[PDB]
Image (cartoon, coloured by chain):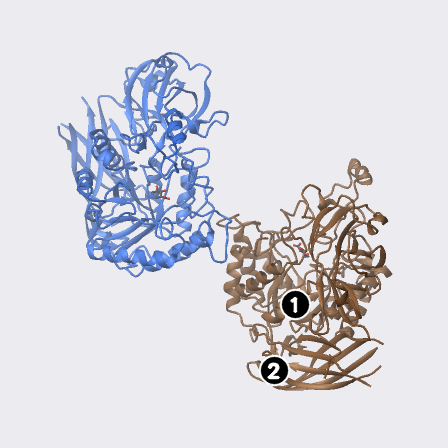
Chain colours: A brown, B blue
Amino acid sequence: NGMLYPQSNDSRIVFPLDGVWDFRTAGEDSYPAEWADAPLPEPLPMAVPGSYNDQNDELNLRAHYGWVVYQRSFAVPSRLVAGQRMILRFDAATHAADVYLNGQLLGSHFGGFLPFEFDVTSALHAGENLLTVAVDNRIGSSTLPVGNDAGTAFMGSDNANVPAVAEAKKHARRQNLPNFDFFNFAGLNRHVELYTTPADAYIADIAITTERLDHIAGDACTAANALIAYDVTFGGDGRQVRISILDGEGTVVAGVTADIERTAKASGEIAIRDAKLWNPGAAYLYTAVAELLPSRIIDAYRQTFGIRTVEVSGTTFLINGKPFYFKGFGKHEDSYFHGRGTDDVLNVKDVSLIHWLHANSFRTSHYPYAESMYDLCDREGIVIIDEVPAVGMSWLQYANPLVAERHREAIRGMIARDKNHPCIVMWSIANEPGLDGDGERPRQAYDYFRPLYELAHASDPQNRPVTLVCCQNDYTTDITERTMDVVCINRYYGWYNLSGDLDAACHALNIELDFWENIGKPVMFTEYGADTIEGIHGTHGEMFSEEFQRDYYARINAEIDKRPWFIGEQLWNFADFATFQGIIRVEGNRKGILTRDRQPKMAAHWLRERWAGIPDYGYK
Amino acid sequence: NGMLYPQSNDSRIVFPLDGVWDFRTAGEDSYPAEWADAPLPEPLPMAVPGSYNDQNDELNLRAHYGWVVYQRSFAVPSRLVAGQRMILRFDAATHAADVYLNGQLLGSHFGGFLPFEFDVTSALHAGENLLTVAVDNRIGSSTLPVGNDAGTAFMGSDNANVPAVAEAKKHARRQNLPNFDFFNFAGLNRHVELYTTPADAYIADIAITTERLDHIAGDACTAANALIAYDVTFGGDGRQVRISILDGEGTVVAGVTADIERTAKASGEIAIRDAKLWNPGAAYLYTAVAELLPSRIIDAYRQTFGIRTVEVSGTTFLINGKPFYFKGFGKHEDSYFHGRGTDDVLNVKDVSLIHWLHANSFRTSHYPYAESMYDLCDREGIVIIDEVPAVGMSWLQYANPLVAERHREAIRGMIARDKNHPCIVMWSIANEPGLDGDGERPRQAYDYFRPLYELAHASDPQNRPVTLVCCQNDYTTDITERTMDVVCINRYYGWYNLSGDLDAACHALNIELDFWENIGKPVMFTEYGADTIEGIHGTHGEMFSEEFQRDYYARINAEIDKRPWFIGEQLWNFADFATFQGIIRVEGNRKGILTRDRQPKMAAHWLRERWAGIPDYGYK
Ligand SMILES: O=C(O)[C@H]1CNC[C@@H](O)[C@@H]1O
Ligand SMILES: O=C(O)[C@H]1CNC[C@@H](O)[C@@H]1O
């Protein structure tokens, strides 16, 4: 279950395998087996990590349907593999992968946004090793995220009653049709690395929780006492682990030696006096150093954490007992050449833009992001809502056992990967599933999602709030969204309805806010916005102008400011991003307040001024 | 000398000749004179009024050098012409024109921005008449506006030391090289019309002046008494003219009968009790109706006017005795298909944008505008600085008597055309002539311009202030600008110098403002700005971004606000406009706060908010 990010220390070394690999496209539903057994014939270069789709302009890899095959060679000194346990980790392969080393199948994985690994201790040999990775991009009614098996991509146009169209559909080239509004970027989107651990006994997992804070300071910077809990899991085979707690300067401030008991596990609690708390806008990180003891150390791992509590109380969202207000947006992992490929230069820039805007938060719309972004937000004081790739779902998916299992895998896998981050304050178990309607449909949706809500709570040792991000719907027949811990709504009054009429949009919004006012839950926007082409201007801004986007937020935000139970504003989107092509997507989704190259539109400046005057705590 | 705009009434009729004419291009230095004798061979269509340059995409008329020939036919009933004096009026033919009617050369005109007319009574005949107009676009060292005889256009790039460049220049196609930063649009840019007056005696010119205001209300809306004077000139041959003054509702509020004395003139004064004054932001217009008396009326003309005084006093600019502050910009007559062609839809729209912006004024950079725009600003309460086409001048021109004569012609013609407009508060006798330097250059410039300053004063019966718009220069050796009635300066600190460094730009500006503080004259900007491409954005705006343009005005305006003697801010420009092509002009000049299609950039919104808070009177 543990998926600790690979670390190098006195006991452990990481050997990255990123770089320019060999690559070939393959078939709609197969690829040649012999490509795992010998060097790829006539290979193309392909950089990893990165989506493959925008890395070759001679081919139209955006249109590719099915498999591709990556390959590279590598060699490491026998000295450093001798006696060690050898693990090959894929941070992400989107969506499914088969992995081979030296002509041997290592195994496969489904799930394009979470890491997986293989023990290669026995498949490795000295000299050059040949690593082959086949990656499948296909999506459909059984995948998360969901594809459409026929018809159109999400918000695509059709003339389905025209006989010629119906007939041409039967013979059209197979293409993935996302039931979600972002491009289906595929390939080795995140890092690949070989790493070592000791073989006889090793640290497999660590969970740190903030159990209780006694007497939090008025400014929330410290607490008189913090009770933290640790849970260390071991692999391999009267043994002990030493746990040292280091503060922000590396000083040892606490330490215990705990007994390992047979899963081999050690768990306990540690009191940290005068603890320095983690807050939005004021991060503070500790390190838990776990050392497996035999003066010598057998194994070690350093786990960053921050001390803070999260609690929903009535219509408030309390961080360290203080009423928080979210300011931010949904993001995407999306950029020009990389596609969905992780890029830490861009992550660093985006975090600085979050600060420039005076925002404090975002959601990982619509899939878990690369692990390095959460470390960055841990150090930079930015709060995250962590979301699984359960986007595009409807009643067709609720009746499918395979989908339900993939959904539980994604929830368990996201929380197992991300549980130690102090920046994560809430889990989202889906984006815009179908919840409303007549007959049994609302109850069917509820019966599908309630066990997943329970699973997210059971899986997280911090027991953080759980939400489900709700599409614009008939809120009077949806019986699911109102049962979440925080109500997170996506609304486009004045854009997809009441188009351009901000008076009517605000009237409609206020009618629905009157509905939520009586529910007793904290409510926030997780999306709202307007497609905007930079450089389109008007004195009376119409849809797609920079002025209309600014006016849109000015009018809507004035209405939610009147509601004390409305605890956050996350807009859509941080920045323009790529989508499947169609008649409503002008080079992708243009609801960004920043352009795809991260330049600010008029509305970004307006928002920056607004958010500069809204405090993280106590706004409401 | 009078050029009253043609009017239709019981004594007079106007027959417009606009529409789609026939057109041919001709030679660099000649056209076929026989084209006036018969319909043009194989003619192109060409709408009038309009520049010709953008009306044909099969030809490259922007590259044309030399002559073109317009032609059309017309017929009018014998009853219309019988007994009448028939005048053919060209509102503007840019730059020079030869006019033929039924093969007879009527005459020629130089000066591309002011009207001229011919008596055609004897050249007309019954049935179809054939009107042929040859128009010359050429500019050079003796024209106003000034062209360069060799080298490059204004702020063009060159590599003049490369031998191949020097040689190719000798054989390059002839092309006009503007020594001014706007495109040399040519042709019948303004209306053409045939009009009638009585033949025996007729009204030839009217001047109305505001002589004195007694007891002006605190809000300047009225005066207890206003003394106005009239001066009517007659043509033809104990006769009398009735002068009636009509208020805003058409009510005759005053009337006098004057004796015509011989060059036939009638002159006198009228006192208007509780006169409603014309003010920026609060226009009020009277009509002076002059009726030539024999029961019957022989001739009549209705002249609009507004009652207001203009006086420079110390460092203030007094309208109706109140300290005025200019808010506005230089403009251009420039638009997509029309070029420099007059377009009243666009004039109406532009005056509404001036109100939207909360501006109160503009300058007719860099030529007299179409007459209809001044009538519009009369009714809409927008102040005008009226400027002759003396742009591009330096010491080569001051030594040329043909240029001095053309310059005197332009000044007399502008003031004779425009003297009755209340919206005009100041005359500009040149834009950015060479004034500074060493040796005898500063004195030579002074001796050239001082007589023209005196000429503008002698020509205007209202005796309004006279300025010269000064280019960015060494203000310590320029001895001419400081002798103007208002000092009008164009400054581009932080754009063309100290580029992008707004701290240094403001420091430089303050050093020069310290200079003008000691001179003791009222000072205003007539230009300052930054080229800006809509849709270019940055968090720290660099040159060409929307943010830089906004920051430019925010920083510069903060500095002039500290100077009580700085009486106005006219920026460059209202809207992006066309120029000769070159390496610093991205589809023309982009210093507009509006795009060429009149859409607001970020700076326009900022300036609108600034100008909303600055009163027309009493800001300083
Ligand atoms: O339509 C939109 O702009 C948004 C609607 N909510 C879901 C987003 O993925 C999508 O991009
Ligand atoms: O350089 C500029 O942008 C301006 C400088 N002053 C004169 C203007 O005609 C010109 O357009």
In-image side of A366 versus A202 (left or right): left
**Depicted A315 relative to depicted A442: above or below:** below
Residue denoted by label 1: A374
Answer with mark 2 or mark 1, whichever residue precedes in sequence. 2
Q: Amino acid at mark 2?
A: Thr
| Residue B567 placement (x, y as % from top left) | 28, 54
Which label is found at residue A251?
2
| Residue A600 placement (x, y as % from top left) | 53, 56
In the image, A256 versus B126, the foreground residue is A256
The residue depicted at 46 percent of the width and 55 percent of the height is B541
- Asked if one can make out residue A399 in the rendered structure from this viewpoint, the answer is no
Taking the image as four quarters, which one is ligand 1 found in?
A: bottom right
Q: Chain of mark 2?
A: A
Under 8 Å from ligand 1: the CB of mark 2? no
Mark 1 packing: few (<14 Cα in 10 Å), some, or many (20+)? Answer: many
Q: Find the distance from the CA under tag 2 to the CA under tag 1.
A: 24 Å
Element type at mark 1: helix
Q: Quadrant of residue B110?
A: top left
Give the position of the C terminus of chain A as an image quadrant: bottom right
In the image, A185 versus A124, the foreground residue is A124
Give the position of the N terminus of chain A as an image quadrant: bottom right
| Residue B525 placement (x, y as % from top left) | 31, 50
| Residue B268 placement (x, y as % from top left) | 16, 38
Element type at mark 2: loop
Q: Quadrant of residue A455?
A: bottom right
In the image, B618 versus A363, the foreground residue is A363
**Depicted B303 relative to depicted B541: above or below:** above
Q: Amino acid at mark 1?
A: Tyr
Q: Chain of mark 1?
A: A
